[PDB]
Image 1 (tube, protein in one colour):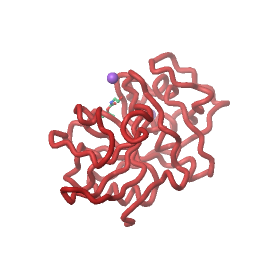
Image 2: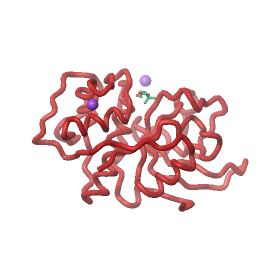
Image 3: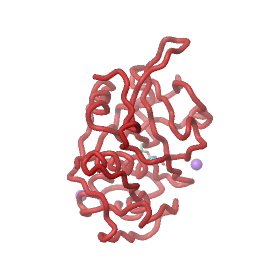
Amino acid sequence: APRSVDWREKGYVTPVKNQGQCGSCWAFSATGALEGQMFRKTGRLISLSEQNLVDCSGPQGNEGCNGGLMDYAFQYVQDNGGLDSEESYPYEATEESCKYNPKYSVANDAGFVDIPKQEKALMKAVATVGPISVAIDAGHESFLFYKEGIYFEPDCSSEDMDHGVLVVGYGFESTESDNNKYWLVKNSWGEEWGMGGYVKMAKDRRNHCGIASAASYPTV
Ligand SMILES: *[C@@H](O)CNC(=O)OC(C)(C)C
Ligand code: NA
Ligand code: NA
């Protein structure tokens, strides 16, 4: 596979968004992955509505601001036959009744693909598909204050994830400890967090923070 990949350079990735004080991380991860696959299909980058997923994808198993799963969101889009644009169905950071309107749908999918729970399989998927939805353990103060560098948290769990994010690539940089490899991860806490809203997560350090344990993407 390539040693470095950055799907932002190829135009697959919208700007960083902010979920606010709602547990909708899973909706931002899913829109990010579908935004990439729709651009790969059509050549158009269109920002998609998280509020649409928060309000409407409960029948697929999601729970609004109390959590959800990207795969449940991809299933909703398939079941529903559409997903509205971000401009048409803006984000309010609170759960409300479903207001989906197919006239303003700009995306679709036909299911999704779950990646084997190995970082090597995640690398192959990032290298060949585009941005991938992933779940991580972000429940540590170090993750809140992250500014730059390769994030490594020794108390991070590989099994108990609490936050959905989006792998847009991977790469490397020389470090003190010679643990030089990272996943390039888009968060949804605004661009003031981390590095313009991105974080470099330690790669090939034993599935650090669980980044390869629930990885998937939508099929378009
Ligand atoms: C993020 O706002 C809420 N966390 C969440 O839904 O975690 C997973 C279920 C692990 C995606
Ligand atoms: Na919070
Ligand atoms: Na279903």
